[PDB]
Image 1 (cartoon, helix red, strand yellow):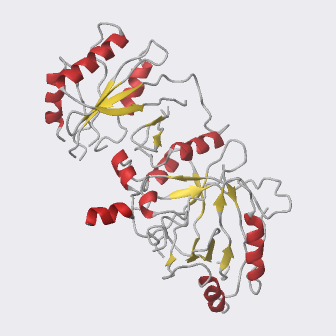
Image 2 (tube, chains in turn purple, red, cyan; image 1 turned 120 degrees about the vertical axis):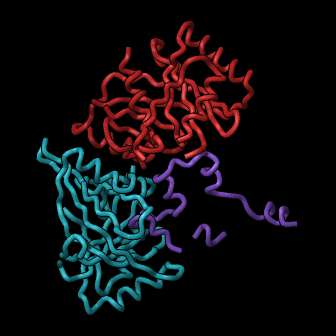
Length: 50
Length: 174
Length: 180
Protein backbone atom coordinates (compact mmCIF):
# COMPACT_ATOMS: atom_id res chain seq x y z
CA UNK A 1 0.00 0.00 0.00
CA UNK A 2 2.98 2.30 0.60
CA UNK A 3 4.41 1.44 -2.83
CA UNK A 4 1.16 1.90 -4.76
CA UNK A 5 0.79 5.33 -3.10
CA UNK A 6 4.47 6.32 -3.08
CA UNK A 7 9.24 3.87 -8.91
CA UNK A 8 9.01 7.63 -9.50
CA UNK A 9 6.12 8.71 -11.77
CA UNK A 10 8.04 10.49 -14.56
CA UNK A 11 4.87 10.47 -16.72
CA UNK A 12 5.85 13.04 -19.35
CA UNK A 13 8.23 15.62 -17.85
CA UNK A 14 7.14 16.21 -14.23
CA UNK A 15 3.34 16.46 -13.74
CA UNK A 16 3.99 14.36 -10.62
CA UNK A 17 1.13 11.87 -10.87
CA UNK A 18 0.59 8.14 -11.45
CA UNK A 19 1.38 6.14 -14.59
CA UNK A 20 -2.02 4.45 -14.84
CA UNK A 21 -3.69 7.74 -13.88
CA UNK A 22 -1.73 9.61 -16.55
CA UNK A 23 -2.67 6.95 -19.12
CA UNK A 24 -6.32 8.15 -19.03
CA UNK A 25 -5.51 10.52 -21.89
CA UNK A 26 -4.23 8.08 -24.54
CA UNK A 27 -7.37 5.94 -24.22
CA UNK A 28 -10.86 6.72 -22.96
CA UNK A 29 -11.08 3.66 -20.72
CA UNK A 30 -14.51 2.34 -19.75
CA UNK A 31 -16.09 2.96 -16.35
CA UNK A 32 -14.96 -0.56 -15.40
CA UNK A 33 -11.29 0.31 -15.93
CA UNK A 34 -11.87 3.69 -14.24
CA UNK A 35 -13.08 1.83 -11.15
CA UNK A 36 -10.25 -0.73 -11.47
CA UNK A 37 -7.72 2.14 -11.41
CA UNK A 38 -8.04 1.98 -7.63
CA UNK A 39 -9.04 -1.00 -5.46
CA UNK A 40 -9.81 -2.03 -1.88
CA UNK A 41 -7.49 -3.77 0.59
CA UNK A 42 -7.10 -5.05 4.14
CA UNK A 43 -9.95 -7.21 5.41
CA UNK A 44 -11.29 -8.05 1.94
CA UNK A 45 -8.02 -9.56 0.70
CA UNK A 46 -7.45 -11.71 3.79
CA UNK A 47 -11.09 -12.84 3.73
CA UNK A 48 -10.88 -13.87 0.07
CA UNK A 49 -7.58 -15.65 0.76
CA UNK A 50 -9.00 -17.61 3.70
CA UNK B 1 -14.33 -0.94 -31.61
CA UNK B 2 -16.26 2.33 -31.65
CA UNK B 3 -18.89 1.66 -34.32
CA UNK B 4 -20.39 4.65 -36.12
CA UNK B 5 -23.77 5.93 -34.93
CA UNK B 6 -26.93 6.03 -37.04
CA UNK B 7 -29.26 8.87 -37.93
CA UNK B 8 -32.90 8.59 -36.76
CA UNK B 9 -34.24 7.21 -40.06
CA UNK B 10 -37.50 6.23 -38.38
CA UNK B 11 -39.49 9.45 -38.01
CA UNK B 12 -43.26 9.08 -38.27
CA UNK B 13 -44.57 10.22 -34.89
CA UNK B 14 -43.81 12.16 -31.70
CA UNK B 15 -40.13 12.15 -30.70
CA UNK B 16 -41.09 11.30 -27.12
CA UNK B 17 -43.42 8.57 -28.38
CA UNK B 18 -40.67 7.36 -30.73
CA UNK B 19 -38.19 7.09 -27.84
CA UNK B 20 -40.84 5.30 -25.79
CA UNK B 21 -41.47 2.79 -28.59
CA UNK B 22 -37.72 2.26 -29.03
CA UNK B 23 -37.29 1.58 -25.31
CA UNK B 24 -40.28 -0.78 -25.37
CA UNK B 25 -38.79 -2.69 -28.31
CA UNK B 26 -35.43 -2.87 -26.52
CA UNK B 27 -37.13 -4.24 -23.41
CA UNK B 28 -39.07 -6.77 -25.49
CA UNK B 29 -35.77 -7.90 -27.02
CA UNK B 30 -34.42 -8.20 -23.47
CA UNK B 31 -31.80 -5.93 -21.94
CA UNK B 32 -30.73 -4.16 -18.74
CA UNK B 33 -30.36 -0.54 -17.67
CA UNK B 34 -26.65 0.22 -18.15
CA UNK B 35 -26.99 3.76 -16.80
CA UNK B 36 -27.57 7.08 -18.51
CA UNK B 37 -25.09 9.37 -20.25
CA UNK B 38 -25.09 12.64 -22.22
CA UNK B 39 -23.77 13.87 -25.57
CA UNK B 40 -22.82 17.54 -25.47
CA UNK B 41 -22.58 19.68 -28.60
CA UNK B 42 -21.09 23.18 -28.95
CA UNK B 43 -19.66 24.48 -32.22
CA UNK B 44 -17.13 27.28 -32.71
CA UNK B 45 -16.80 29.03 -36.07
CA UNK B 46 -16.53 24.07 -36.45
CA UNK B 47 -15.10 22.38 -33.37
CA UNK B 48 -18.03 20.48 -31.84
CA UNK B 49 -17.58 19.97 -28.10
CA UNK B 50 -18.77 16.78 -26.40
CA UNK B 51 -18.06 14.42 -23.52
CA UNK B 52 -18.84 10.72 -23.04
CA UNK B 53 -17.29 7.40 -22.00
CA UNK B 54 -15.40 9.02 -19.29
CA UNK B 55 -13.59 12.08 -17.94
CA UNK B 56 -12.48 13.30 -21.38
CA UNK B 57 -13.78 15.67 -24.07
CA UNK B 58 -13.43 16.36 -27.79
CA UNK B 59 -13.74 19.39 -30.05
CA UNK B 60 -12.44 19.43 -33.61
CA UNK B 61 -13.61 21.21 -36.76
CA UNK B 62 -11.51 19.08 -39.13
CA UNK B 63 -8.52 17.22 -37.67
CA UNK B 64 -7.21 13.71 -37.02
CA UNK B 65 -8.84 13.43 -33.60
CA UNK B 66 -6.50 15.46 -31.38
CA UNK B 67 -8.30 14.39 -28.17
CA UNK B 68 -6.40 13.35 -25.10
CA UNK B 69 -7.65 16.09 -22.76
CA UNK B 70 -10.38 16.17 -20.14
CA UNK B 71 -13.24 18.67 -19.92
CA UNK B 72 -11.32 21.19 -17.80
CA UNK B 73 -8.03 20.71 -19.67
CA UNK B 74 -9.77 21.87 -22.87
CA UNK B 75 -12.17 24.40 -21.33
CA UNK B 76 -9.28 26.34 -19.78
CA UNK B 77 -7.49 26.49 -23.14
CA UNK B 78 -10.73 27.58 -24.83
CA UNK B 79 -11.32 30.35 -22.28
CA UNK B 80 -7.69 31.42 -22.67
CA UNK B 81 -8.36 32.16 -26.35
CA UNK B 82 -10.92 34.86 -25.53
CA UNK B 83 -9.95 36.74 -28.70
CA UNK B 84 -8.04 34.20 -30.79
CA UNK B 85 -10.61 31.45 -31.38
CA UNK B 86 -13.55 32.65 -29.27
CA UNK B 87 -16.38 31.87 -31.70
CA UNK B 88 -19.14 30.86 -29.28
CA UNK B 89 -22.17 31.22 -31.56
CA UNK B 90 -25.73 30.10 -30.77
CA UNK B 91 -25.60 27.01 -28.55
CA UNK B 92 -25.72 23.89 -30.70
CA UNK B 93 -28.44 21.36 -29.84
CA UNK B 94 -27.25 18.38 -27.80
CA UNK B 95 -28.97 15.06 -27.12
CA UNK B 96 -28.88 12.69 -24.13
CA UNK B 97 -30.58 9.55 -22.85
CA UNK B 98 -30.15 6.26 -21.06
CA UNK B 99 -28.02 3.31 -22.16
CA UNK B 100 -28.82 -0.41 -22.33
CA UNK B 101 -26.76 -3.52 -23.12
CA UNK B 102 -28.19 -6.81 -24.36
CA UNK B 103 -24.87 -8.68 -24.54
CA UNK B 104 -21.35 -7.44 -25.37
CA UNK B 105 -23.14 -4.47 -26.95
CA UNK B 106 -24.60 -1.10 -25.95
CA UNK B 107 -27.42 1.10 -27.25
CA UNK B 108 -28.08 4.80 -26.73
CA UNK B 109 -30.84 6.99 -28.17
CA UNK B 110 -30.94 10.79 -28.31
CA UNK B 111 -33.59 13.42 -27.71
CA UNK B 112 -34.41 16.95 -28.81
CA UNK B 113 -32.61 19.85 -27.10
CA UNK B 114 -34.72 22.88 -28.03
CA UNK B 115 -37.61 20.74 -29.29
CA UNK B 116 -37.12 20.87 -33.07
CA UNK B 117 -34.07 18.59 -32.84
CA UNK B 118 -33.29 15.01 -33.81
CA UNK B 119 -33.51 11.81 -31.76
CA UNK B 120 -30.52 9.90 -33.14
CA UNK B 121 -29.24 6.56 -31.84
CA UNK B 122 -25.75 5.23 -31.17
CA UNK B 123 -24.47 1.64 -31.06
CA UNK B 124 -21.00 0.10 -30.81
CA UNK B 125 -19.34 -3.32 -30.61
CA UNK B 126 -16.53 -5.15 -28.81
CA UNK B 127 -14.39 -6.33 -31.76
CA UNK B 128 -11.59 -4.37 -33.44
CA UNK B 129 -14.37 -4.58 -39.00
CA UNK B 130 -17.30 -6.74 -37.84
CA UNK B 131 -19.65 -4.34 -39.64
CA UNK B 132 -21.69 -7.29 -40.90
CA UNK B 133 -22.35 -8.91 -37.52
CA UNK B 134 -23.61 -5.73 -35.83
CA UNK B 135 -26.09 -5.12 -38.66
CA UNK B 136 -28.30 -8.14 -37.90
CA UNK B 137 -28.86 -6.70 -34.41
CA UNK B 138 -30.65 -3.62 -35.74
CA UNK B 139 -32.23 -5.67 -38.53
CA UNK B 140 -33.96 -7.77 -35.87
CA UNK B 141 -34.55 -4.68 -33.70
CA UNK B 142 -36.15 -2.28 -36.19
CA UNK B 143 -36.86 -2.00 -39.91
CA UNK B 144 -34.67 -0.53 -42.64
CA UNK B 145 -32.04 1.63 -40.94
CA UNK B 146 -28.37 1.69 -39.89
CA UNK B 147 -26.55 2.57 -43.13
CA UNK B 148 -23.24 2.55 -41.24
CA UNK B 149 -20.91 3.96 -43.92
CA UNK B 150 -17.65 3.37 -42.01
CA UNK B 151 -14.23 4.64 -43.03
CA UNK B 152 -13.40 1.55 -45.12
CA UNK B 153 -10.10 1.04 -46.98
CA UNK B 154 -8.19 2.93 -44.28
CA UNK B 155 -6.43 0.09 -42.47
CA UNK B 156 -9.30 7.13 -39.90
CA UNK B 157 -9.50 3.75 -38.17
CA UNK B 158 -11.56 2.21 -35.32
CA UNK B 159 -13.76 5.31 -35.55
CA UNK B 160 -12.52 7.44 -32.65
CA UNK B 161 -15.12 10.21 -32.28
CA UNK B 162 -15.48 10.06 -36.07
CA UNK B 163 -19.26 10.14 -35.62
CA UNK B 164 -18.94 13.89 -34.95
CA UNK B 165 -19.00 14.58 -38.70
CA UNK B 166 -22.42 12.95 -39.06
CA UNK B 167 -23.48 14.63 -35.82
CA UNK B 168 -22.66 18.09 -37.18
CA UNK B 169 -24.28 17.15 -40.50
CA UNK B 170 -27.56 16.30 -38.75
CA UNK B 171 -27.25 19.43 -36.60
CA UNK B 172 -26.92 21.61 -39.71
CA UNK B 173 -29.98 19.91 -41.22
CA UNK B 174 -32.51 22.21 -39.55
CA UNK C 1 -7.26 27.59 -11.77
CA UNK C 2 -3.64 26.96 -10.79
CA UNK C 3 -0.46 28.88 -9.99
CA UNK C 4 3.19 28.76 -10.99
CA UNK C 5 6.45 29.15 -9.07
CA UNK C 6 10.14 29.29 -9.95
CA UNK C 7 13.50 29.39 -8.19
CA UNK C 8 15.65 29.98 -11.29
CA UNK C 9 19.43 30.05 -11.09
CA UNK C 10 22.67 28.58 -12.39
CA UNK C 11 25.80 26.81 -11.16
CA UNK C 12 29.23 25.92 -12.52
CA UNK C 13 29.97 22.58 -14.16
CA UNK C 14 32.66 21.39 -11.71
CA UNK C 15 30.31 22.22 -8.82
CA UNK C 16 27.46 19.82 -9.53
CA UNK C 17 28.41 16.65 -7.65
CA UNK C 18 28.04 17.99 -4.10
CA UNK C 19 24.97 19.94 -5.24
CA UNK C 20 23.06 17.01 -6.76
CA UNK C 21 24.19 14.74 -3.92
CA UNK C 22 22.80 17.17 -1.33
CA UNK C 23 19.60 17.64 -3.33
CA UNK C 24 19.11 13.88 -3.83
CA UNK C 25 18.94 12.58 -0.26
CA UNK C 26 16.18 14.95 0.86
CA UNK C 27 12.77 13.40 0.09
CA UNK C 28 13.49 10.76 -2.55
CA UNK C 29 12.65 7.12 -1.81
CA UNK C 30 15.35 5.50 -3.97
CA UNK C 31 16.70 4.98 -7.50
CA UNK C 32 17.37 8.50 -8.82
CA UNK C 33 17.02 8.79 -12.59
CA UNK C 34 17.30 11.31 -15.42
CA UNK C 35 15.71 12.20 -18.76
CA UNK C 36 16.52 13.78 -22.11
CA UNK C 37 13.84 16.09 -23.50
CA UNK C 38 13.08 17.37 -27.01
CA UNK C 39 12.72 21.03 -27.95
CA UNK C 40 9.60 21.93 -29.95
CA UNK C 41 9.11 25.48 -28.68
CA UNK C 42 6.46 27.03 -30.91
CA UNK C 43 4.59 30.33 -31.10
CA UNK C 44 0.87 31.02 -31.64
CA UNK C 45 0.35 34.65 -32.66
CA UNK C 46 -0.07 36.99 -35.62
CA UNK C 47 -3.11 39.09 -34.73
CA UNK C 48 -2.32 41.20 -31.64
CA UNK C 49 1.53 41.32 -31.45
CA UNK C 50 1.25 39.37 -28.16
CA UNK C 51 2.49 35.76 -28.47
CA UNK C 52 1.14 32.88 -26.39
CA UNK C 53 2.92 30.27 -24.28
CA UNK C 54 3.51 27.67 -27.00
CA UNK C 55 6.69 26.11 -25.57
CA UNK C 56 5.62 22.59 -26.58
CA UNK C 57 8.84 21.04 -25.30
CA UNK C 58 8.11 17.38 -24.60
CA UNK C 59 10.52 14.59 -23.71
CA UNK C 60 11.73 12.21 -26.41
CA UNK C 61 11.80 9.28 -23.96
CA UNK C 62 9.94 5.95 -24.19
CA UNK C 63 6.75 6.23 -26.24
CA UNK C 64 3.20 5.74 -24.99
CA UNK C 65 3.36 8.78 -22.73
CA UNK C 66 1.40 11.69 -24.25
CA UNK C 67 3.04 14.99 -25.13
CA UNK C 68 1.73 18.21 -23.57
CA UNK C 69 2.50 21.87 -22.84
CA UNK C 70 1.99 24.10 -19.81
CA UNK C 71 0.97 27.74 -19.66
CA UNK C 72 3.87 30.02 -18.73
CA UNK C 73 3.60 33.68 -19.70
CA UNK C 74 2.29 37.13 -18.80
CA UNK C 75 3.48 37.32 -15.17
CA UNK C 76 0.52 38.75 -13.26
CA UNK C 77 0.88 41.24 -10.43
CA UNK C 78 0.13 40.52 -6.77
CA UNK C 79 1.79 37.94 -4.51
CA UNK C 80 1.98 40.25 -1.49
CA UNK C 81 5.01 39.21 0.59
CA UNK C 82 5.41 36.15 -1.63
CA UNK C 83 7.63 34.84 -4.42
CA UNK C 84 7.01 34.80 -8.18
CA UNK C 85 3.45 33.80 -9.06
CA UNK C 86 1.61 33.54 -12.38
CA UNK C 87 -1.57 31.83 -13.57
CA UNK C 88 -0.66 28.55 -15.29
CA UNK C 89 -2.46 25.59 -16.84
CA UNK C 90 -1.84 22.13 -18.31
CA UNK C 91 -3.39 20.10 -21.12
CA UNK C 92 -2.35 16.65 -22.34
CA UNK C 93 -2.86 15.69 -25.98
CA UNK C 94 -2.54 12.59 -28.16
CA UNK C 95 0.87 11.37 -29.29
CA UNK C 96 2.08 13.47 -32.25
CA UNK C 97 -1.48 14.73 -32.81
CA UNK C 98 -0.69 17.92 -30.89
CA UNK C 99 2.06 18.98 -33.30
CA UNK C 100 -0.20 17.91 -36.18
CA UNK C 101 -2.93 20.31 -35.07
CA UNK C 102 -0.34 23.01 -34.31
CA UNK C 103 0.98 22.82 -37.88
CA UNK C 104 -2.58 22.67 -39.24
CA UNK C 105 -3.55 25.79 -37.26
CA UNK C 106 -0.74 27.82 -38.86
CA UNK C 107 1.79 28.41 -36.08
CA UNK C 108 5.56 28.93 -36.11
CA UNK C 109 8.44 27.71 -33.97
CA UNK C 110 10.29 29.62 -31.26
CA UNK C 111 13.48 27.69 -30.41
CA UNK C 112 15.31 24.47 -31.22
CA UNK C 113 17.70 24.20 -28.26
CA UNK C 114 17.29 21.13 -26.06
CA UNK C 115 18.08 21.16 -22.33
CA UNK C 116 18.45 17.69 -20.82
CA UNK C 117 19.17 17.12 -17.15
CA UNK C 118 18.09 15.31 -14.00
CA UNK C 119 14.93 15.28 -11.91
CA UNK C 120 14.47 15.02 -8.15
CA UNK C 121 11.35 14.07 -6.20
CA UNK C 122 10.77 16.69 -3.50
CA UNK C 123 7.98 16.66 -0.92
CA UNK C 124 5.00 19.01 -1.13
CA UNK C 125 7.06 20.82 -3.79
CA UNK C 126 9.11 19.76 -6.80
CA UNK C 127 12.51 20.69 -8.23
CA UNK C 128 14.15 20.19 -11.63
CA UNK C 129 17.50 20.90 -13.28
CA UNK C 130 18.75 20.99 -16.87
CA UNK C 131 21.56 22.37 -19.03
CA UNK C 132 21.01 24.01 -22.42
CA UNK C 133 22.50 22.13 -25.37
CA UNK C 134 22.83 23.62 -28.85
CA UNK C 135 22.51 20.55 -31.07
CA UNK C 136 20.74 19.40 -34.24
CA UNK C 137 17.44 17.48 -34.47
CA UNK C 138 18.88 14.02 -33.65
CA UNK C 139 22.15 15.24 -32.08
CA UNK C 140 24.39 26.76 -24.56
CA UNK C 141 25.00 28.57 -21.27
CA UNK C 142 27.30 25.72 -20.18
CA UNK C 143 25.76 25.80 -16.71
CA UNK C 144 23.16 23.62 -15.00
CA UNK C 145 20.17 25.88 -14.42
CA UNK C 146 17.94 24.80 -11.54
CA UNK C 147 14.57 25.95 -10.20
CA UNK C 148 11.63 24.95 -7.98
CA UNK C 149 8.82 24.11 -10.40
CA UNK C 150 5.52 23.43 -8.64
CA UNK C 151 1.88 23.83 -9.69
CA UNK C 152 -1.13 24.13 -7.40
CA UNK C 153 -4.48 25.96 -7.14
CA UNK C 154 -5.03 29.09 -5.04
CA UNK C 155 -5.62 27.31 -1.73
CA UNK C 156 -3.62 28.99 1.03
CA UNK C 157 -0.37 29.75 -0.86
CA UNK C 158 1.52 28.97 2.35
CA UNK C 159 3.99 27.03 0.18
CA UNK C 160 5.91 30.28 -0.40
CA UNK C 161 7.33 30.12 3.13
CA UNK C 162 8.33 26.49 2.60
CA UNK C 163 10.03 27.40 -0.69
CA UNK C 164 11.89 30.22 1.05
CA UNK C 165 13.00 27.82 3.79
CA UNK C 166 14.24 25.38 1.15
CA UNK C 167 16.12 28.19 -0.62
CA UNK C 168 17.66 29.06 2.74
CA UNK C 169 18.69 25.42 3.08
CA UNK C 170 19.87 25.48 -0.55
CA UNK C 171 22.23 28.37 0.28
CA UNK C 172 25.72 27.54 -1.10
CA UNK C 173 25.47 27.57 -4.90
CA UNK C 174 21.83 28.34 -5.74
CA UNK C 175 19.14 30.92 -4.97
CA UNK C 176 15.67 31.98 -6.14
CA UNK C 177 14.74 34.68 -8.66
CA UNK C 178 11.73 35.89 -10.62
CA UNK C 179 11.48 36.72 -14.35
CA UNK C 180 10.10 39.65 -16.35
